[PDB]
Amino acid sequence: TGKELLLVLYDYQEKSPREITVKKGDILTLLNSTNKDWWKVEFNDRQGFLPAAYLKKLD
């Protein structure tokens, strides 16, 4: 389930079936940050992976 809010810092185009597409300024929720570089997130009707470097954890 969703935890911390996340801010998208730059547009990102999904590069695999496991990723999602987001736009700069989008607000997401965090699902899995076990890996420092790749985070699972939830955004509206979709869940998937994004590069952690593109995201600011809002805590």
Image: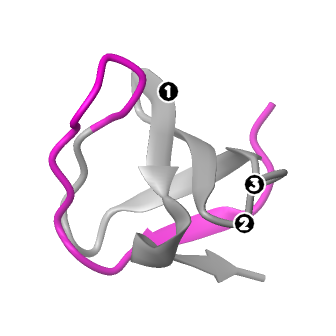
Within 10 Å of the Cα at label 3, are there few (<14), some (14-19), or many (20+) other Cα atoms? Answer: few
Left/right of residue 43 with respect to residue 26 in the rendered view:
right
Which part of the image, by quadrant, shows the N terminus? top right
Q: Secondary structure at mark 1?
A: strand
Q: Nearer the viewer, residue 45 or 48?
A: 48
Residue 24 sits in quarter: bottom left
Q: Are marks 2 and 1 in contact (CB under 8 Å)?
A: no
Give the amino acid at mark 2.
Answer: Lys
Give the amino acid at mark 1.
Answer: Gln
> How far apart are labels 2 and 3 at the CA level?
4 Å
When the figure is inspected, residue 40 is found, relative to residue 11, above or below; the finding is above
Mark closer to the chain start, 2 or 1? 2
Where residue 35 is drawn, which disc sits there? 3
Residue 14 sits in quarter: top left
Q: Nearer the viewer, residue 25 or 40?
A: 40
Q: Which residue is mark 1?
A: 47
Q: Residue at x 43, y 62 (%)?
A: 27
Mark closer to the chain start, 1 or 3? 3
When the figure is inspected, residue 42 is found, relative to residue 8, above or below; the finding is above
Q: Nearer the viewer, residue 38 or 22?
A: 38
Q: Which residue is mark 2?
A: 36
Give the amino acid at mark 3.
Answer: Asn
Give the dominant element type of the magenta stretch: helix, strand or loop: loop
Residue 28, x across and y down, in percent: 50, 54
Q: What is the tally of numbered marks visible in this picture?
A: 3
Q: Residue at x 62, y 51 (%)?
A: 39
> How far apart are labels 2 and 1 at the CA level?
18 Å
Magenta residues, as a range? 1-20
